[PDB]
Amino acid sequence: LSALNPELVQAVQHVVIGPSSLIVHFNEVIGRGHFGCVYHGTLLDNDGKKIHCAVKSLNRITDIGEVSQFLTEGIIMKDFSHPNVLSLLGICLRSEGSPLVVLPYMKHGDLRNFIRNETHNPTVKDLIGFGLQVAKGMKYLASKKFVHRDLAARNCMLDEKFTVKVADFGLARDMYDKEYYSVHPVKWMALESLQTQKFTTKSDVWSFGVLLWELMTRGAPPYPDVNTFDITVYLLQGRRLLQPEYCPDPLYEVMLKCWHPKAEMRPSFSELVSRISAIFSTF
Ligand SMILES: O=c1[nH]ccc2c1ccn2Cc1ccccc1
Image (cartoon, rainbow, N blue to C red; front, side):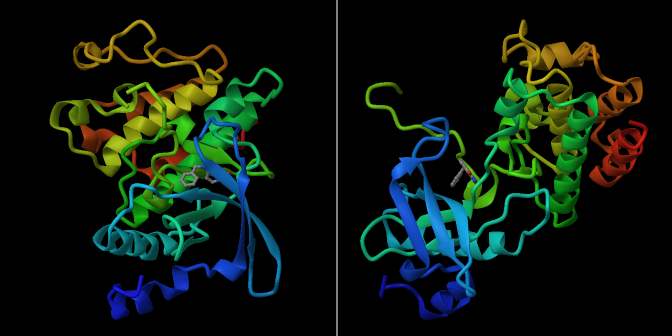
């Protein structure tokens, strides 16, 4: 680590968690395998408050060029903070072992598994509230010109107060990468992204519309009968996800606006917050 550029070391200092500030519980995983090797940890703040965190070791980082790029990603993501976006608590640069990413612990795991869980019974109002929270998190990301590229219910998380956090971006990416011993998002993508492999805030709006559909169906898979290959033709014919049984008509109108074939015709996330907040307030 002494081979690191000193001005970059100075720049990342405010993101770095010293080893005496963090107690990593490498003996216990969070999500019992659902998220791979993500560990419980305890972070000590400056007042000695104990903070429950999720810790991941980044084994793909093997050389000093990759460590330096990682430091930079930490610097950038530390400036992203919003009630509905997963925050970065910090990073660890270890003398012994791969670097660590430290995030806030999410008591209720991912939003898709939460809504699919038969034991949980969120109301239509609660489901719309989750959608509004995601819209607020994306309004924040879009306001900083950050394009998510993989928005879906599986990629959002829930804390102990049931606050939704948009996740799976920056150092929280690769949320479901699992390591196997012997084994080797087209249905959320905007039509133009399927065609050009380019992503924008307007393609995140399309994905948000599919996430809204997931919320109102309590986590049903979209287009279950359509092969991923055939999705482009299906959308070009003007076919779209149908209105879920318990979805209010003005909310389905919002979903349809998200899937307009012309990206410029789709609402902005600011407009989505405006429209969904008014719908939410009728319940
Ligand atoms: O309780 C949690 N809080 C925040 C993130 C998170 C969990 C569980 C899995 N994950 C995903 C992830 C963790 C670390 C690094 C990268 C991705």
